[PDB]
Amino acid sequence: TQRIASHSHVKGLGLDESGLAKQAASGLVGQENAREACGVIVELIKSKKMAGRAVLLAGPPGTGKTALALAIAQELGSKVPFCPMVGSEVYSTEIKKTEVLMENFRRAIGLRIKETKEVYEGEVTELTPCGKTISHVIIGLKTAKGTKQLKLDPSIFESLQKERVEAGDVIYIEANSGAVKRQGRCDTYATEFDLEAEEYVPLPKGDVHKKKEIIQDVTLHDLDVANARPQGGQDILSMMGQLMKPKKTEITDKLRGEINKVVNKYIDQGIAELVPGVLFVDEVHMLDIECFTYLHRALESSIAPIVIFASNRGNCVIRGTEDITSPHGIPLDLLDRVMIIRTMLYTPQEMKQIIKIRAQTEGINISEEALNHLGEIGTKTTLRYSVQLLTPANLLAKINGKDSIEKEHVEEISELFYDAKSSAKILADQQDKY
Amino acid sequence: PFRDARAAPDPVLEAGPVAHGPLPVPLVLDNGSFQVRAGWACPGQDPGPEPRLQFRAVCARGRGGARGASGPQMLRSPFDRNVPVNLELQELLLDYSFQHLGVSSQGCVDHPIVLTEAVCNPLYSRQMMSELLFECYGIPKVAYGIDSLFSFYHNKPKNSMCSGLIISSGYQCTHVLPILEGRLDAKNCKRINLGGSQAAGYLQRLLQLKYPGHLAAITLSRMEEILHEHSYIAEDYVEELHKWRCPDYYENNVHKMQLPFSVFNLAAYHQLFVGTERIRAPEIIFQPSLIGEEQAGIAETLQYILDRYPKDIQEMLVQNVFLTGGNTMYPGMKARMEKELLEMRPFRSSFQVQLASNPVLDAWYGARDWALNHLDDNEVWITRKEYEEKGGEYLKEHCASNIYVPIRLPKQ
Ligand SMILES: Nc1ncnc2c1ncn2[C@@H]1O[C@H](COP(=O)(O)OP(=O)(O)OP(=O)(O)O)[C@@H](O)[C@H]1O
């Protein structure tokens, strides 16, 4: 099964059809004003027209900023690029800071490219090359569902010959990609020698010829990277590619001009369609003033994705300015470019609902007499500490041979693992021994 | 347990059950190395009321010449490889059949016959056979045709020209007979030199070497029971014998074929546990390298004869794969054949596998329906006087008979 995670319960913004928030829906609770604002942002991203337009989720630690940014990702689903990054990812050692922003801005714009995936596989019954050299190669394929012949081009035949294929081998051919894989000798020839250094696979119990309309997802950053440096070019099958290790590199703005001019030439043909996505620059207060000042170009540019920032800092110093305090840890010049969404501390009842949603996601049965205690301990501490007690409390209940949390399990865990503010009191008392 | 086979029935008749209408009523005669079967054609009767004289084609006679046990009663047989190649036994085999069918009065057999023969028949064998049949038996007109194509002729919808593969399997050969608008395509037709006799001989030899404690208690005439009754052809052999590898499936399917009784007695009166042996013997015609023979077998031959045709004419003969002859009695034979065929037909293409409505007797019912429909034809039969102007190798090329080659035989 899947692993439960710090957000695996949020499945959408949970808005109703009017765009107003339900009190508790799609795994979220409370937070209605910010959820309604994110509803407008999901409509903005679904509308595709806009470029570089950006949003700041602002508010205290443990108030749902990353849960709402992932709720936006879930409202859009896999069909639209959502690229998460921490502001701390910008400090590369192979490329400049203001390149890592542009790479991640280019990861958040997608191409959607349909093709009919067309697979042939089976025992090769014959290979017969047919100009006077090779016009085409006839190949025959067999499976326990029938037989076909294909008219391969000479470049696919070079690939059969590189895969060291012979009559009676079981082959996978893909007719779009020109990919070829030998899978083994067909086991009808497994008696050809008593030991030979080959693996024999049974003749495929499946169709000689299979079709899907696959729907490929790719991003402008995949294009930028795979076209900037000379490709590895060979399917391993080489040793020049041992010498020059790759590095990340400062892809020039002049190449991106041509990648844009080429993608326009393909989306005009309907061969691809664009999916403008979201870049989630999580914890943006960790960007430096040079990174922040580069956003004052990147949010203006007519190509850029939608950008979601998040921050929890007060009136603190802007990273890399050595002096200048500014709200949310962001320069006022950038804070004048983003639509800010507030985020709020919950009432105890709204925490108690999250504790139950966590329990019923995380696989815990919990009695009301213990859920009331986690609701109270949330007010004594913080929401994330209460939630973190659930698996430990269930795991003591399981060791104690019980099917559910009861008061004594959460009460024992409370006296066993400290929170960030009870532990700070220990360090303030024993100040001379740490 | 085994049973034991019958012997010495009383199928005695008058001068003959000669039917009404036109004067001639032919004998329908089927010769094969397992059984001879013969009956009057019984014209105007829709079901044949009796394919008379079912008996094993093996005979004996006294060491003083005093008596001849030709009927179902050591012994000898007039065939080699399912073609007749005898005189002195072939006569007493015919005599028994005519004597039980009824003889009219004079110094010949009374009325015309259809005599079943090998797919191709060596010219000398038809010469020797027609020489017996005109010198001794004096039949007024004679038809030669093939057991397999007769059983196909019965199983047709109509008296119509057809195309198909006859997958035939008699006592000492199995043959793939491609046919094109009723013509047997003998130019590229093929056979495997194996059949029920060699599978039964193999099943004997298996149990001899499994049970040296009683080599005398098993016998070929008992192997013929477990080969017809309890043996089956695999859906695919390398998977069937793989499910035979585990003791739970083995114990659920291994057969208590007891010998007749007078330690738990089984050292002298074993239950003769047959497991993979009830598969191995059937597989001989598909995989004749089980008996060491280098022949291609019934699956690779069907590929080899079929791929020699244009693609657009392979279809309307795979549209009638027709299973016939004694070995097609096996349960699962259709289900195997349609897999071996699915594994070699073009990916979406259709095929049809038909089994003879009786796996074996349809050769005779086919020759009956054929003789009933062709009774009053002139050009279809060798008429007695034609044997003074054609050497006895001669054939009339009617549907359900071989090609004729314009030829003669030197003799003195
Ligand atoms: N409906 C909800 N409303 C608010 N918070 C929720 C909700 N559902 C989940 N969360 C909680 O979000 C918490 C973790 O992400 P959160 O957004 O609170 O982090 P944050 O401190 O505010 O921001 P950051 O990711 O920058 O640290 C988890 O405790 C999770 O249970």
Image (cartoon, coloured by chain):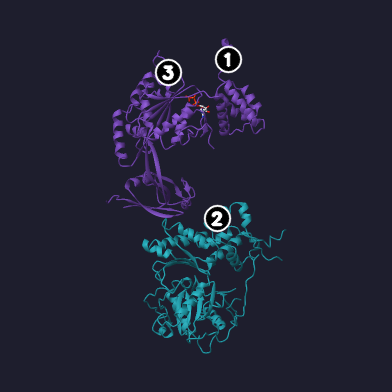
Residue A219: % across, % down: 37, 35
Can the viewer see residue A8? Answer: no
The CA span between labels 3 and 1 is: 29 Å
The CA span between labels 3 and 2 is: 77 Å
Identify the secondary structure beneath mark 2.
helix
**Image hue for chain B:** cyan
Q: Nearer the viewer, residue B85 or A26?
A: A26
**Image hue for chain A:** purple
Tell whether A135 sits left or right of A216: left
- Which mark identifies residue B240? 2
* In contact (CB < 8 Å): disc 2 and disc 1: no
Tell me which amino acid carries mark 1: Lys
Name the residue carrying label 3.
A327
Tell me which amino acid carries mark 3: Pro
The answer for which chain carries disc 1 is: A
The CA span between labels 2 and 1 is: 75 Å
Residue A195: % across, % down: 49, 47
Placement of B352 over or under A39, stated as above or below: below
The answer for which chain carries disc 3 is: A
The answer for which chain carries disc 2 is: B
Q: Are marks 3 and 2 on the same chain?
A: no
Q: Are marks 3 and 1 on the same chain?
A: yes
Placement of B309 over or under A156, stated as above or below: below
Placement of A369 over or under B396, stated as above or below: above
- Which mark identifies residue B246? none
Crowdedness near tag 2: few (<14), some (14–19) or many (≥20) residues, C-alpha within 10 Å: some
